Image 1 (cartoon, each protein chain N blue to C red):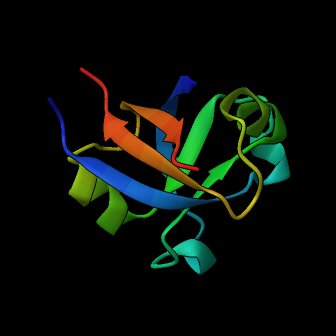
Image 2: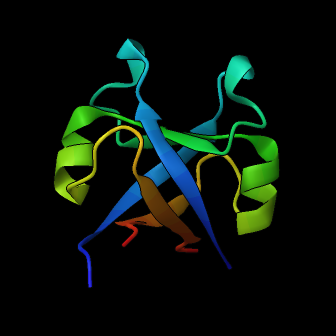
Length: 44
Length: 46
């Protein structure tokens, strides 16, 4: 399952953490939980 | 076909809930070759 989301800037405490911040409904679309890994890629 | 990056899912800040965004830092954006405001495609690894 996949979704397309708009890139927004990190909060400063997140910089360098290798995280993506996504809300509950976005995680539910994806089938992921906090702490799971996702694959991210630029959209043409 | 664009390069892919693997990242850890974390919860959204509350003001962002419902916005349809992902927050990622600059080194992640550079790795993807995106700027703030472009779209990315996200897919579960697990």
